[PDB]
Image (tube, rainbow, N blue to C red):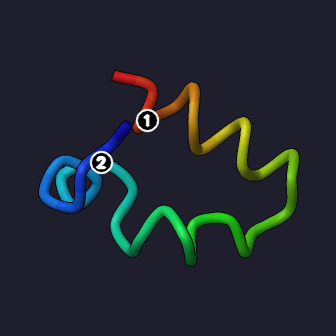
Amino acid sequence: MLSDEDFKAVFGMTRSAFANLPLWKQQNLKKEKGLF
């Protein structure tokens, strides 16, 4: 699970807020980042 710090250097905002974009935008920004 992307711990706060890790998330930081991954998406930009927070994973909680990260789940506010469109679901297709989610899986995308994900495999695009936060997947590692």
Q: Earlier in the sequence, mark 1 or mark 2?
A: 2
Report the residue at 86% width, 45% height from top. Answer: 24
Q: Which residue is mark 1?
A: 33
Kind of element beneath mark 2: loop
Q: Residue at x 55, y 71 (%)?
A: 16
1 and 7: which one is in front? 1
Q: Quadrant of residue 35?
A: top left
Most distant residue in the left direction: 5
Say what amino acid the circle numbered 1 marks: Lys
Q: Is 19 rendered above or below residue 2?
A: below
Q: Which mark is residue 10?
A: 2
Report the side of 7 relative to 14 (left or right): left
The correct choice, above or below, for 2 with respect to 14 in the image is above
Say if mark 1 contacts mark 2, CB within 8 Å: yes
Q: Is residue 1 above or below residue 16?
A: above
Q: Position of residue 4 (x, y in %)?
A: 22, 61
Q: Quadrant of residue 14?
A: bottom left
**What is the x, y in percent for residue 5?**
13, 58
Q: Residues within 10 Å of mark 2 (few under 14, many from 20)?
A: some
Q: Residue at x 18, y 47 (%)?
A: 6
